[PDB]
Image (tube, rainbow over the protein chains, first blue to last red):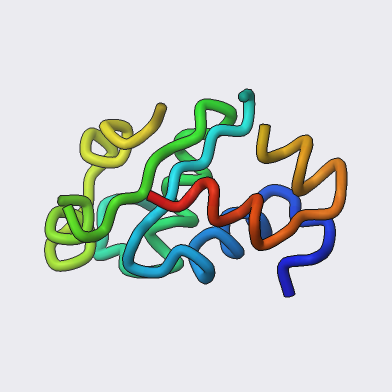
Length: 30
Length: 30
Length: 21
Length: 21
């Protein structure tokens, strides 16, 4: 489900699901 | 809308809305 | 951590903004 | 950045896992 265009809240949701208990960092103006 | 219990995807959604273009870091086992 | 402060207990805008970049 | 690689262009599991902690 990750091999598509993922924007805005949909990208954050994918990070949440993939990274699990690790957590993640979301830096859009990088 | 932030002064409540925010768990799982609902917490990540709140961070997304509050932090905006800054982005955020989500570290649950901290 | 954020889960203890915002999920197990009531969150706040102060707490959330601590996790913005 | 992640928006250029996963929103403006097609994402991948490799890219996403680069942003896990």
